[PDB]
Amino acid sequence: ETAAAKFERQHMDSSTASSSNYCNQMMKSRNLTKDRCKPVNTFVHESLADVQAVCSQKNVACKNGQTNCYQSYSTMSITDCRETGSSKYPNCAYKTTQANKHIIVACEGNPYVPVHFDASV
Ligand SMILES: Nc1ncnc2c1ncn2[C@@H]1O[C@H](C(=O)NS(=O)(=O)C[C@H]2[C@@H](O)[C@H](n3ccc(=O)[nH]c3=O)O[C@@H]2CO)[C@@H](O)[C@H]1O
Image 1 (tube, rainbow, N blue to C red):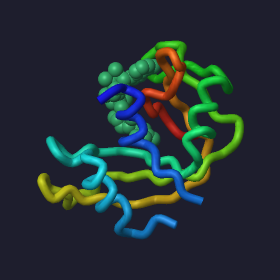
Image 2: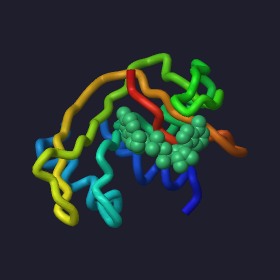
Image 3: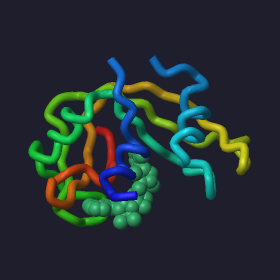
Image 4: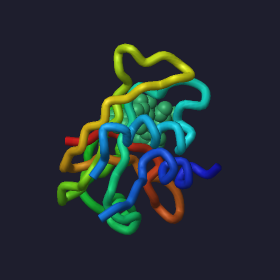
């Protein structure tokens, strides 16, 4: 799996919504609960073209100190998945929360594409 492909699997769910069951099902189907319960994960509902375009938008500092992060000029429809208190592997359990926020992604490679989801603001 390429880094670009991993980003698409972990963070992209293009749709033009999310039920209380959404994260429980999506974290499983996208193979994010295979080894452990991933505590926090965000899905983005805008088009792949729109998210890829963020790599040419506002340059901002990455949480890790690198300079290859970019913030979206427009807000984007997203869903945050957060592990519940009662959640126990292999039965990982999640709270589903919809939001409309600017996203921050890290980009790499040629083509220069998103490889990491840094934050929403
Ligand atoms: N500039 C870079 N350029 C290139 N690569 C970079 C760069 N920076 C990191 N990586 C890489 O990413 C890898 C990854 O393991 N780091 S991770 O912070 O823990 C991933 C998290 C984050 O996606 C997720 N989260 C978080 C908030 C939110 O709203 N939504 C949401 O989904 O939760 C995860 C845990 O935080 C690491 O191996 C490192 O090499």
